[PDB]
Amino acid sequence: PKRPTTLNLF
Amino acid sequence: DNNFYSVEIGDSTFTVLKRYQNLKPIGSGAQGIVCAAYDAILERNVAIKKLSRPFQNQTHAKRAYRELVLMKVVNHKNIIGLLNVFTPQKSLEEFQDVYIVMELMDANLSQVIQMELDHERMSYLLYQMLVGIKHLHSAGIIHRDLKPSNIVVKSDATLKILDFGLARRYYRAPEVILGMGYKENVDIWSVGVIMGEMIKGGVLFPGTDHIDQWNKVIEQLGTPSPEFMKKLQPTVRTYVENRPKYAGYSFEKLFPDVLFPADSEHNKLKASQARDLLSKMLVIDASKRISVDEALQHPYINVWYDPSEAEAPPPKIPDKQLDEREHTIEEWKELIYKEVMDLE
């Protein structure tokens, strides 16, 4: 279950 | 010259260390306007927030003091990092502004609510808030004012909490808005709302003032228990007890599948667990509302659980400080000043 590392601030 | 210097950002004058260049206004958190700046020494984007004569008034000073001590003594991957504080005035005589320099994040949650998260994001973000919150709490600090404006995120999916210049519109727990008397899970309502908002993708209770919420809130969750109404002030019980009465809706009908993303490859990251957690958090009666630990232990959240994130040693206050007194103008100034000078 891996921690996200990206997040799109569009 | 004297280390400092002055730029006009609109009507506001920022006076700051020469190392801080290229200030851009980025917004205003409760008690101060905030600039983004380039920090020429660290070679890094930073954020500078100014409190113009924070000793001005009883309110202001209580909060600025809280914020100062706290920002020093509290440190954690999920709480905005302090980098520098200063005043540019060279004496207690002449002292009036405080400048707090912090890390600069990419965005406040306002914002994440707007976009279309998968489950591991929604969960992980929430996990991070909860962990930051558990940290505050472990040193008997209760934020009471958590909301998307005062929670920031980064484009690597880290989240940090700003603010204790309130810590000690309808995101505030009912126990709080009803002069009722509170406890640590007063912060869990906040999260419940925010999560609710993350799922819905917009405002959870399309409601204007700090009691037009109330109706939209009770309309939806349902009128709170009789033997919760007691607990209220006779002053207030009358008002609440008088409102129309609502059954509420189930959490399935309030947060239905269609609003959630696809059930992840992972066992626990599912709309039924999200709904579960939510219905345990977004509860009106605080003594029926989940604590931070339970939320952390909850199948939707615990997938990320890390003892070294979640069980760090509490910040330690002098408990000499715990705003146990009111003051006069002069004293506050001195206190703040001592505190700020202490921070240089």
Image (spheres, coloured by chain):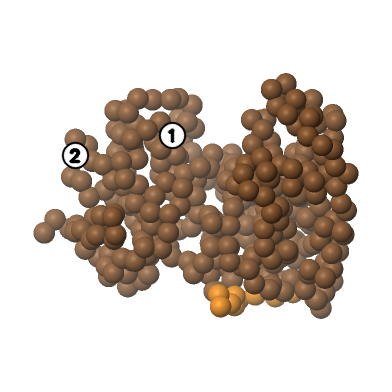
Judged left or right of residue B235, residue B226 is: right
| Image quadrant where residue A5 sits | bottom right
Image position, residue B41 (x, y; %) = 28, 69
Quadrant in which the N terminus of chain B appears: bottom left
Q: Is residue B19 above or below residue B235?
A: below
Q: Give the total number of marks visible in the rendering.
A: 2
- How packed mark 2 is, by other alpha carbons closer than 10 Å (few <14, some 14-19, many 20 or more), is few
Tell me the residue at 39%/50% (across/down). Answer: B32
Q: Position of residue B187 (x, y in %)?
A: 65, 46
Q: Amino acid at mark 2?
A: Glu
Q: The chain drawn brown is chain what? A: B
| Chain that bears disc 2 | B
Secondary element at image label 1? helix
**Mark 1 near mark 2, Cβ–Cβ under 8 Å?**
no
Residue B172 vs residue A5, the one in the foreground: B172
Chain drawn orange, letter? A
Residue B94's disc is 2
Residue, disc 1: B59
